[PDB]
Image (cartoon, coloured by chain):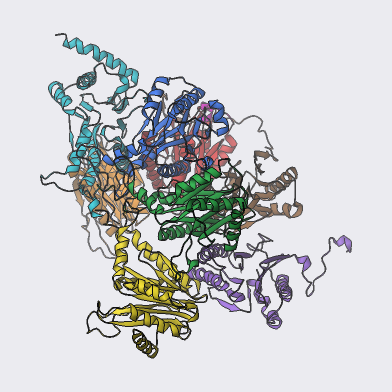
Chain colours: A purple, B green, C cyan, D blue, E brown, F orange, G red, H yellow
Amino acid sequence: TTIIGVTYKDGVILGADSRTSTGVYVANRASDKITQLTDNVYVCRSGSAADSQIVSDYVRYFLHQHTIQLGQPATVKVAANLVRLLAYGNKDTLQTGMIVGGWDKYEGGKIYGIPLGGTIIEQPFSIGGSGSSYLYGFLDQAWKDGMSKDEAEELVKKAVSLAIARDGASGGVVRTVIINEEGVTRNFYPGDQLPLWHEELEPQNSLLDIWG
Amino acid sequence: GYDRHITIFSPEGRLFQVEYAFKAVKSGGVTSIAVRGKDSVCVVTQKKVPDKLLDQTSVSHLFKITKFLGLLATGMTADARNLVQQARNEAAEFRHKYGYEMPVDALARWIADKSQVYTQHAYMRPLGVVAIVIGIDEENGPQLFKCDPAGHFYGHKATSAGSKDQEAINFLEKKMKNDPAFSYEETVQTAISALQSVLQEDFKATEIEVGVVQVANPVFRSLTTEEIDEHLTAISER
Amino acid sequence: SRRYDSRTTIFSPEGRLYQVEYAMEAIGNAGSAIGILAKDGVVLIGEKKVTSKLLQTSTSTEKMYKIDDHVACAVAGIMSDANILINTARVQAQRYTFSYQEPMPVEQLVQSLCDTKQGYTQFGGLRPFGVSFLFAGWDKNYGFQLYMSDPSGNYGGWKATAIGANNQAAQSMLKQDYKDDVTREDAVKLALKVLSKTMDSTSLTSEKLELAEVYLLPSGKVKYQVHSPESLNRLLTESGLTQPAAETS
Amino acid sequence: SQYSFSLTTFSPSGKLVQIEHALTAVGSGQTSLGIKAANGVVIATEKKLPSILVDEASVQKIQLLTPNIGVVYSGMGPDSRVLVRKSRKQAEQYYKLYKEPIPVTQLVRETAAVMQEFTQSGGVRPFGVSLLIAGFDENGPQLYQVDPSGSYFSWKASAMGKNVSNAKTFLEKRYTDDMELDDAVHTAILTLKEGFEGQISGKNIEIGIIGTDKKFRVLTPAEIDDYLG
Amino acid sequence: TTIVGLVYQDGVILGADTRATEGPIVADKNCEKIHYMAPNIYCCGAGTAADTEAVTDMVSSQLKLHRYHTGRESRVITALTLLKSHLFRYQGHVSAALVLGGVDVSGPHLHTIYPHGSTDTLPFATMGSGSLAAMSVFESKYREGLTRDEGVKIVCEAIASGIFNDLGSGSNVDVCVITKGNVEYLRNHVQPNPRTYTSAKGYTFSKPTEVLSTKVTALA
Amino acid sequence: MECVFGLVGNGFAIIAADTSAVNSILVHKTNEDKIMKLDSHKLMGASGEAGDRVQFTEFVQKNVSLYQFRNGIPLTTAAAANFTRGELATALRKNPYSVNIILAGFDQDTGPSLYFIDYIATLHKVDKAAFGYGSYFALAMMDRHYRSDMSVDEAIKLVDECIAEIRTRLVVAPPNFVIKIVDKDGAREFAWRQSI
Amino acid sequence: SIFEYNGSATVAMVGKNCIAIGSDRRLGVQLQTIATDFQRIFQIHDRLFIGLSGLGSDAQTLYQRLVFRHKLYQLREERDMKPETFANLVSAILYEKRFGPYFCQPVIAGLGDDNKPFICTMDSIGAKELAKDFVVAGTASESLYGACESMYKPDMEPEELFETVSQALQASVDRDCLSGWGGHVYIVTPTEIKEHILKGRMD
Amino acid sequence: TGYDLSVTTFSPDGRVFQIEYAAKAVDNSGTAVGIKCKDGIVLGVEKLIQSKMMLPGSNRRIHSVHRHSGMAVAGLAADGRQIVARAKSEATNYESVYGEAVPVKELADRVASYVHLCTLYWWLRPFGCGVILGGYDRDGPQLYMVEPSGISYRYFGAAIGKGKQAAKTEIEKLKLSEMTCREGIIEVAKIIYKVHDEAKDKAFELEMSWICDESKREHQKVPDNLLQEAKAAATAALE
């Protein structure tokens, strides 16, 4: 698994990898690891599938209640703190690591990384899932604060594809979710659209097209 | 005996406390009406501030139970807020537990069932609030419903609540004898007009509040005072 | 909230509980039923109070219920509460047969039910059950037994007793006519006679009656059985013929 | 929360007064009736609404609890909903435990016990409703009645609500065994017409019928009008 | 076991074999592995049987009660969410795992539910021991917009692959076709491996089978 | 560790048991009588953890006595055995007692009976029973010489033989056994088998 | 394990309009043979029998508890419970203890409806195995499966059914050391119930 | 006539008399004024000295609820403390769960819901106190007032107790949109002094708390110097 969140001038561009595995078998190739909490806040689910899914459901429920009570678009900070309410409340049972991103008139686009165990860390970007480790070195020399929706999109695609190419637990299509003042924009990048990194070849239908 | 004081059957079979709750609704001076159209549902009531001090935006009887459900509460304001909190808790719980938006008829039925409880348990005074629920059912089209302190939810094509029940009903069914199919603008203007014909006075589009739904825009919405004023002008010139 | 409390469980200045006495009155207003403890069995007969002609009557019983393979009861009073009490009584009998693996002796079943009733009679502030039971059954301990339960939660064994409407007249005729060694047929005849003589209407109608008898089959098996309407017709005709067969002189 | 003081005590005459008030309260409810043909059952009630503006289609008085069973109420509407909900719950518990439909008699007994509960428990009033539960099952057609006292009976035909006595006598004189289901439907419609002030129409009354071995179905106005035509 | 789910152009097709085993011995040659939940929802159960029938039956009853309460036809998301809420709170101890399918106001639906409450939404799903044998066929032959006959062909091929290639599942193939209105269920659509021997002359029980006592009852 | 065994004659049901109470290696006592009297017409030999044996046996005797006085008619042997089994089986999954029980009794209308009740709460109406390491020798010898119509002389001879073998062949051979008989007259002590 | 603490062998097999249910006859601590006349088959009503293989104590408890529920059903409904319904009841009351299970492997067999046989055995937590040719449970599971698979026929008169179930049970129990010491076979027909006790190897 | 004896009993007029008796208890208490200035909120309370030996500062009636808001209670003070405690509880609980300071509007809504709930129960005495919240949110200053019946609305000025009518009339004669909280101090002091009537009641001590921008949006007492000069000005304003 891989989940990355990038903050650009206007908002967030949360990301994912799409591969729920049960051992060495790939039970699902197009899992959706980014879920909605409100129209402006999304969480990158990672870790245990059941635990992350239900924490997403419960946060969405509490956050519906909250946004009706206030009659007002719920903020990112509150979404992250609600995710922590359950991540920390259930340290024993929930083996989940998540990244929460969104947009507000109050504070703009913010990313809150709730790692395993239940801390909240506002960050310029976050990395999670088992595929994170292949990225620390790359991101540290890549992150430039204040990017556009474009450069941030390319960087998220590069990060998730580099993690995909090298990690057993991460693969499939790259999914990204651009959250902004105008609203969420969900994308889908199969392997064919992603670049080709060290010692990888261009996909070809059949060897009969080259011979050997 | 005690039956005048608590919700137990009177010697002739009436529950007097529920009746007194109805009287409490008709108290308070306010009256409200709703008109279900072909394409929309409009719900309208009158609000009035006696003081310069009281902020006018803090007083209103339209409540957004859900982005796609509304509710107009007639009765005691505190009870109206209690019932509103209960319904908001139910709507969110229904969507959570069952995975889809709660339909209007379900909200009305749940409110009515909750109200029935006060009517059977002796030491729980029935809520003195008649609540009108509007929403556009995803499959049944526009909906309108009315729940009373007794607990008799029934679905109404058009209805009234408050101190002027009968006058509003008579005007509405006079204007609706033909079983019409009201356009949006026609629906909302019929509601406003039936309020006018009950108050016997004009109103500056400020002492009135309107809430509407539309199939083209299911969100329960409260009209801008300028839209209310445009509807007033349209009523004037015909 | 205090002022709304009737204080059901409380002693009157006379030293007696009012609600239970009102319960006995409610029994007195209910349909009559009597029991005959015969040598070879026990017979319960009951009066169906509601006798509109549109009633179906295809249901086997309205006042007598089976509580176990060896015990049955005839109910008088508020049948609504009697349903609950019979449900409990069946449950208690099965609880004994589970714990000990054998039929629950009748006297114990009666006593457990009466202990249920006395609870409402003594604490909690709920109205007592307005019911009264006649129990018929058989044990290895004592053989055929007949018991009567007051809504006070009190009970006693009776060779022949009656409950419900017009109780005391039937009681008196049972005093005058019941004898030891009354067999199956004699018990049935005596019950029919005493009831009809206690009924407002002679030449009774099978649709307005119920007769049940807990006897012992030749092979030591307690067989409870409630007579079908045609069997009631046969007995009614035989009794309406035998009554003049004695009154002729 | 003591609320443990029976508000339905025994009057000095032995009568349970509050239950009697409940029986009157149903006595002032809209009429309903039911007949059992030799090969099916029929229940109907009057559904006259205070105004045309009330959408009659948004609520039904005849409701089916299990595909075999349906009920009609007279008296307070809100209480009938409580009882229908609880009876449906019990039917589904029975089906969970035994994978069979609950027999009509058992459902009636359980609903009656629910009725009785409120006539002994403290802090509550008995239900101002009486039910006609029509069902057809493995041992023939059945029509059961339930009243706020919690007692239940099996009727060949019955009625309750406004205009009980006239409908009752009408049924008693006009009922007969071997009546077919359609004859019963016509008879029920006629009985409603007897006391029904105004003129009957498919949008004024409600009818439900169980055929032979089939499911309880509530007639739609499009076809009730055909029956009454 | 081998259970399968495919969403074709009009609706969702479910499939399953009919072998049930208890260790290395087949207890039941013809098991009913596709279950009814609602007029438009069926589910193939894999994992611990007792748990699968218990949970599917409980959800079926809840869904029927909700159908009465709201009147309108139940939808699949409701079944999915009820199954999630039940399975999770038992933390996977109840080891029921299902493929769930139906057709609703929103159109065909197909989900896989795992004992911990993790769910997926998929165009093709497989579970049970032969899940790999089936997913071979799906990853080779699935495509969008299969017609009902092609879709049923593919599901039958997948189940046959999961019969012949995996020992846990065998016997006969069953299928449930869930279109908009009608659910065409097949009790034993494909019986691909008949009994190979006749046994010729039946064998005789030489030992007369001595018996000591015989109580006999004249049942009515 | 305890040894217990039973035997049903023509009109009597004998129960014998070792009378040694121990801790680890010390016979704190050799007069520990373990066969209880539930009634005038019942015996209940028990084997198992001494504390559990005593507590469970006393509990069952309490319930038997409560039934007797309340109704006026004593529990029949089969009902006493079934009640014991029910209580033991219910405790099995909640706070198990580690007692094995052999219940004998006489009822005028049924005759002598001997019930097998295991600490797992399996109940069976056995002709002959035995618990503990002496069970093997007791059962084999009874099978070898048992008949269905034994005079109390023959039954006691058989029990003496079983005791002698149990002493001779076990390593934990207890020296002292008590023999109790139930007949029409009532549960009783027959004889004490002093060895030391 | 705990299932073979006592050891049992129970079989059920379907004839034309008759049903036959068989069983072993011995109680044992593990290998001690306390009693050669144990009962694993219980009649609940004419045309319905339950065999309860597995732990003996769990078996007795479930039998007594089932009698409680069945009698109370007869008093409340006035009909003897139909086989499939009884199997569902047993499944429910076994699954209630999903996490505390009874160690029984019940076999349920009985005629009903229009004189139509019914057989099913269940997991220890109620997973039913509604079958139509035959059902087998106990420690001799595999041996019974082989014996019945090799000895069954589709539609069998009562006498053929008796002989076949008897031979299957005996030949399958002779290959098991925790079971034997006789046999106890019922042939249930819509007009007659024959309860046979068989001569077995007492070793 | 028997109907005025419980909170779960509508009188045939469809009104609950117990709530009105509670509200009367407030009407008998003492004035409490709140004002929504351009740059904050000023709360002021006429506090009556029961005996001259009380210590100036005794039984303070203006309480904080959380960092950015505070209350003034009129009516039965013992109930005012319970409501203040509940407001504190709600503020901190929301802060905990959502990680954000409670919107004063939400705080007032929760407090009002609590007050209303304390009437639905047959076994509770309805609170006999009315309160005023004046938090200074991220949505700006905003003054609320909760009535012993559970109703509440957002005001620009408020008053409760003996001096209801005079206080309201005087407030209306003020251009709240133009006065800074420094001007609000003077205005509220002057109003409280006008509305007091020495000819009827004993002396009193003005107690005022500003939730303004000088107070860094944090509810605090008015500084002693400004309060005393406002007292002197208000005294001078009586002639």
Q: Nearer the viewer, residue G69 or G150?
A: G69
Which residue reaches farthest top? C248
Task: From the viewer's perspective, tell me whether residue A88 is left or right of residue G149.
Answer: left
Is F174 placed above or below G34 here? below
Q: Which residues are magenta?
A: G153-162
Taking the view exactly as shown, the residue that stands out farthest to the bottom is: H225
- Give the x, y percent position of residue C129: 25, 41
Q: Is residue G161 magenta?
A: yes
Q: Is residue E67 in sight in this rendering?
A: no
Residue B104, percent from left and from top: 53, 51
Q: Position of residue G85 (x, y in %)?
A: 47, 37
Q: Position of residue E153 (x, y in %)?
A: 73, 44
User: Is C44 one of the magenta-colored residues?
Assistant: no
H150 over C1 or under it: above or below: below
Image position of B110 with respect to A37: above or below: above
Q: Is E13 on the left-hand or right-hand side of E63?
A: right
Considering the image in quadrants, where does the N terminus of chain A appear?
bottom right
Q: How many marks?
A: 0
Is residue G50 found left or right of C69 in the rendered image? right
Q: Is residue H207 above or below residue F3?
A: below
Please report the residue visible at 45 percent of the width from the left and 39 percent of the height from the top: G51
Camera-side residue: G109 or F132? G109
